[PDB]
């Protein structure tokens, strides 16, 4: 009863793993470099070095 | 890694990678009492024989 | 993180891994390194609730032997990075001891960021706590991170993201 | 035909064995009309194959394991190339032919029963060579015995070493690590370090060479507590004191050459040698952990004139010293204790606040002065007592005025101080510009903020050069402390018990065990005026009249040392 | 071979010995696992991925 295989014992499908398998470093770079802002102001006071 | 990764060198002409043979050079002058024939420097004959 | 044997800084070591019996299981230990603790700074709100809220002002202490030391930072540093100064609890004019806990990421996450401030009412940010490396990985405070967090989308892999692991019945050696 | 009792035995027959039918294998050389001939050989991996001759009882492995346990490990010794050379000069108006052959060491394993050997296994281990020469006129007929050997022979010297196969000195060192160089020339017993023997015939010359064709070498290690004195730990401390860099390697060649006379042949035996280092942990006048480390050295040579059986038993395992007596003691920093550094040179006055990182644990303070002079070092309330060491060879290479150049040197030299942490004292020591100095703060207990105070005492206090003054207060008497080594000074400062410059009393000062000449000074409050001189303390009964209420300081040297501790009476 | 015959030998220049010591510091699996996907992430360079 312990050492017997049912169907579910060899079902390895993982739709998310496939999606992450066809994603290359180029895709990640494009996602990182994709922006919808032509200007996003950033202001910091620091220590007398605004 | 490219620079350090030199191809493996072949062994001595005779064979093996263990040690070269020895030679002696520079017999000392005949002293007053002792011939001093054997007083000489020892050299590894095929240095860098690889 | 492990407290330095001699210097008053925290060295960065590599987590251990399971190597006991099975090749079918692999994980890295978690209950290692210095035991940190978050202490309320002002003790203004009621002591009934001990949950930490976003943007709260805190002390990040850690237990060394039987004493409770505190994490400080240098008031003035030229270079972008600067090693932290772990030392016993005290008051001095050469170090800042106020830390604000922030959550910049908008998407769900269990990470958090720690920022150093001159004072509660001061508007000058000192820098973000993190780790960098020229090897020799160091537990530092960087002013560079201050900008990286604002570059949308937030990078979850940054070195300023922190998580806290308390002992739990669901995890064992 | 054996005297030993029934049982197994391992026997060494000595070096200098020549096999049969192997005389002219390596060839010969011919000289004439005064020509000089040199023939040499090297033994590395092919002419170093041992020859086994076992029996059903003793297999090859059994023979090998037993012998290598008691005698030289030939397996690891044949790996290192070794060379040997011979030289012969032909006479005038004559020709000389000289041929060379190998020489082996003969190790036997036997089983005696009823005082008669009933079995024997024989192992031949290649050791060195041997040259046989003859002056021959052309056409002469030589005896076959000269060319051919039909039976193994012992030429060097008959030997028989059998083994049954069983189935108070006063050291005045302060507490801390020490590395002692006990000398060079050590060799293991039973010829376990014998490079080889060589027989030079009359009128010839011989030589044995370690050409260092391979860097490999074998040190030895023997600890008493592997928890603290590990092999990798001892080697690290050696690098601290003597800056020993190469342990398992070497690139130093050594030769041994003998030119025998024209009357008698000679035998020359070459051994490998070791230098002995001892790493100790001295505590309260007793060693608690010792580790001996034997580093390979440059060999040892013994010359013997060749001269029945004289059955002999193998000597007990151990070492024998052949070099000169030597004892060099060098202190070393304990790596466990932290090391704080003072970057600013001390000019005339400094106050040091002990950092909390020390966590009430002993540590070292590294510092140096900005100008040579006599300095007084103390602590708040004069407690705890301090110890001061001087780095060896510091401030000799890199110098930076004002700032401190941490040479990272760990070979320290004791100067003064007391290991007792319950006593109160201060130090007056002569410090030199550009010289690294260490102060060992012991394990303090009180959480009260302690402080180390430095002062440049340019006044009369300079008379106490390199002295640990101890404030023996509470007088109202048997005070004992650690005894300084010979020629070192120790001082006691005390206030006599309503001072009015009139009341006076008799005081008795004498040393229980160690005799020393000391001087007594009267304080001025600042200026010290001598009140005596050359006051022997070897249980002297003399008494001195001193006014009550006046602070005095008695400084005593160590004329003769006979006890670890020093006891003063008052 | 290098560890048992090359390191011990003292009759050959370090130009070859030290390079060989570093050459064998790495493992073959490291080379097999070395590909352009790592340098693309390191250098942030886009390249064809399919």
Image (cartoon, coloured by chain):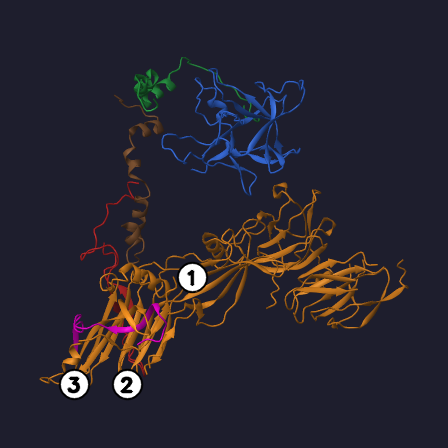
Chain colours: A green, B red, C blue, D orange, E brown
Seen from the viewer's position, the closer of residues D501 and D186 is D186
Mark 1 and mark 3, same subunit? yes
Query: Which label belongs to residue D262?
Result: 2
Up-down relation of residue D34 to residue D549 (above or below): below
Kindly give the residue lying farthest to the top in the view shown: A36
- Tell me: C171 left or right of D424: left
Residue D375 sits in which quadrant? bottom right
Seen from the viewer's position, the closer of residues C150 and D83 is D83
Q: Residue B21: x, y in percent?
A: 24, 63
Tell me which residue sits at (38%, 75%) in the image.
D312
Q: What whole-number distance in Å separates the C-alpha atoms at marks 1 and 2?
A: 39 Å
In the picture of the structure, the residue carrying the numbered disc 1 is: D295
Q: Which of marks 1 and 3 is in front?
A: 1
- The residue range painted magenta reads D1-30
Chain letter of disc 1? D
Chain letter of disc 3? D
Helix, strand, or loop for circle 3? loop
Q: What whole-number distance in Å separates the C-alpha atoms at marks 1 and 3?
A: 50 Å
Helix, strand, or loop for circle 2? loop
Residue C74 is at least partly visible in this image: no
Q: Which of marks 2 and 3 is in front?
A: 2
Task: Count neighbours of disc 2 (C-alpha within 10 A) and say few if under 14, some if 14 to 19, many if 20 or more.
Answer: few
Helix, strand, or loop for circle 1? strand
Up-down relation of residue C16 to residue C126 (above or below): below
Mark 2 or 3 closer to N-term? Answer: 3
In the picture of the structure, the residue carrying the numbered disc 3 is: D94
Q: Residue C44: x, y in percent?
A: 68, 20
Chain letter of disc 2? D
Q: In which quarter of the image is the C terminus of chain B?
A: bottom left
């Amino acid at each position: 009863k312990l050492n017997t295989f049912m169907n579910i014992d060899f079902e390895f499908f993982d739709i998310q793993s496939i999606k992450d398998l066809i994603t290359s470093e180029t895709d990640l770079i494009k996602e990182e470099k994709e922006s919808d802002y032509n200007l996003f102001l950033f202001t910091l006071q620091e220590d007398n070095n605004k | 890694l490219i620079s350090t990764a030199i191809p493996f060198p072949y062994g001595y002409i005779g064979g093996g990678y263990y040690a070269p043979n020895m030679i002696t050079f520079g017999s000392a002058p005949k002293s007053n009492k002792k011939l001093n024939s054997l007083i000489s420097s020892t050299i590894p004959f095929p240095y860098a024989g690889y | 993180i492990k407290l330095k044997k001699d210097s008053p800084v925290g060295e960065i070591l590599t987590r251990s891994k399971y190597n006991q019996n099975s090749k079918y299981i692999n994980y890295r230990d978690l209950y290692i390194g210095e035991k940190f603790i978050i202490r309320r700074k002002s003790n203004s709100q009621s002591i009934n609730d001990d949950i930490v809220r976003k943007e709260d002002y805190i002390y990040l202490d850690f237990f060394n032997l039987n004493q409770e030391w505190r994490v400080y930072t240098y008031k003035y540093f030229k270079k972008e990075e600067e090693k932290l100064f772990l030392a016993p609890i005290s008051d001095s004019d050469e170090f800042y001891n106020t830390i604000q806990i922030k959550e910049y990421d908008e998407q769900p996450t269990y990470s958090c960021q720690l920022l150093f401030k001159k004072d509660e009412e001061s508007t000058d940010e000192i820098g973000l706590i993190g780790i960098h490396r020229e090897y020799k990985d160091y537990f530092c405070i960087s002013k560079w991170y201050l900008k990286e967090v604002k570059r949308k989308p937030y990078n979850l892999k940054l070195g300023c993201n922190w998580q806290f692991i308390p002992k739990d019945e669901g995890w064992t050696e | 035909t054996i005297d030993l009792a029934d049982g197994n035995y391992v026997v060494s027959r000595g070096d200098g064995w020549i096999l049969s039918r192997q005389n002219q294998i390596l060839g010969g050389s011919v000289i004439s009309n005064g020509s000089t001939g040199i023939v040499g050989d090297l033994r590395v991996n092919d002419n170093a194959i041992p020859y086994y001759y076992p029996t059903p009882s003793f297999n090859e492995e059994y023979i090998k394991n037993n012998i290598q346990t008691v005698f030289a490990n030939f397996t690891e010794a044949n790996q290192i190339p070794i060379g040997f050379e011979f030289s012969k000069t032909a006479p005038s108006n004559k020709n000389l032919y000289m041929y060379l052959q190998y020489t082996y060491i003969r190790y036997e394993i036997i089983k005696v029963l009823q005082h008669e050997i009933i079995e024997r296994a024989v192992l031949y281990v290649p050791s060195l060579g041997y040259v046989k020469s003859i002056e021959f006129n052309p056409g002469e007929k030589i005896n076959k015995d000269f060319y051919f050997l039909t039976n193994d022979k012992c030429i060097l010297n008959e030997q028989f070493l059998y083994k049954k196969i069983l189935e108070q000195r006063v050291l005045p060192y302060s507490n801390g690590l020490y590395v002692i160089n006990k000398g060079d020339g050590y060799i293991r017993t039973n010829d376990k370090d014998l490079i080889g023997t060589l027989l030079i015939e009359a009128g010839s010359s011989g030589s044995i060479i370690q050409p260092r064709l391979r860097n490999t070498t074998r040190p030895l290690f023997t600890t008493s507590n592997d928890a603290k004195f590990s092999q990798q730990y001892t080697e690290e401390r050696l690098k601290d004191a003597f800056n020993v860099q190469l342990f398992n390697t070497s690139t130093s060649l050594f030769k041994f050459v003998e030119e025998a006379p024209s009357n008698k042949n000679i035998c020359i035996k070459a051994y490998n040698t070791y230098e002995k280092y001892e790493l100790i942990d001295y505590q309260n006048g007793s060693i608690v952990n010792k580790a001996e480390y034997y580093l390979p050295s440059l060999g040892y040579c013994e010359v013997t004139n060749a001269p029945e059986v004289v059955k002999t038993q193998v000597a007990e395992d151990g070492f024998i010293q052949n070099g000169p007596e030597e004892e060099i003691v060098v202190g070393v920093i304990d790596p466990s204790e932290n090391i704080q550094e003072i970057n600013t040179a001390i000019s005339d006055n400094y106050t040091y606040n002990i950092p909390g990182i020390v966590n009430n644990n002993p540590f070292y303070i590294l510092f140096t002065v900005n100008t040579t002079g006599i300095y007084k070092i103390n602590a708040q309330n004069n407690l705890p007592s301090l110890k001061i060491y001087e780095a060896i060879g510091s401030g000799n290479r890199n110098f930076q005025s004002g700032n401190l150049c941490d040479d990272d040197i760990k070979a320290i030299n004791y100067i003064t101080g007391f290991d007792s942490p319950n006593a109160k004292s201060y130090l007056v020591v002569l410090l030199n510009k550009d010289k690294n100095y260490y102060i060992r703060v012991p394990q303090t207990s009180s959480n009260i903020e302690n402080q180390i105070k430095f002062k440049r005492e340019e006044g009369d206090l300079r008379n106490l050069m390199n002295s640990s003054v101890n404030i023996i207060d509470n007088l109202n008497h048997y005070y004992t402390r650690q005894s300084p080594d010979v020629h070192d000074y120790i001082s006691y400062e005390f206030t006599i018990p309503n001072f009015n410059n009139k009341d006076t009393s008799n005081i008795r000062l004498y040393t229980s065990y160690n005799q020393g000449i000391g001087t007594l000074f009267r304080v001025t409050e600042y200026n010290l005026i001598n009140i005596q001189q050359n006051l022997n303390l070897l249980n002297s009964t003399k008494s001195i009249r001193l006014l009550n209420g006046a602070i005095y300081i008695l400084k005593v040297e160590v004329t003769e040392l006979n006890n670890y501790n020093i006891k003063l009476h008052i | 071979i290098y560890e048992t015959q090359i390191e011990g030998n003292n009759a050959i220049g370090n130009d070859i010995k030290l390079r060989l010591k570093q050459k064998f510091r790495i493992n073959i699996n490291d080379i097999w696992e070395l590909n352009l996907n790592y340098f693309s992430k390191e250098f942030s360079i886009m390249m064809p991925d399919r």
